Image (cartoon, rainbow, N blue to C red; front, side, top):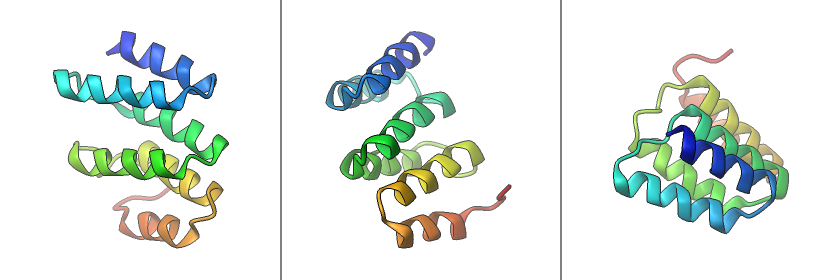
Length: 101
């Protein structure tokens, strides 16, 4: 998992988001579960670069995995939607969260 997280983070910091997405998909397909660091790296770059389509796709994976309770991940979702100008989606994530900080 650290191997995937390390290369995904490097690609995200470099703005190579299509490549990062393909690695994220490969992770999931092999059964190497993304963790809060995986989601954080991708969503942070989506927020920085306005990558709304990738951020929405990642949101779909969050719902599949068991991260519907992770505050770090849901904070990163709110930040991504916010920075992309989708404040109604951001508010919805906030509203569905069991525990905010």
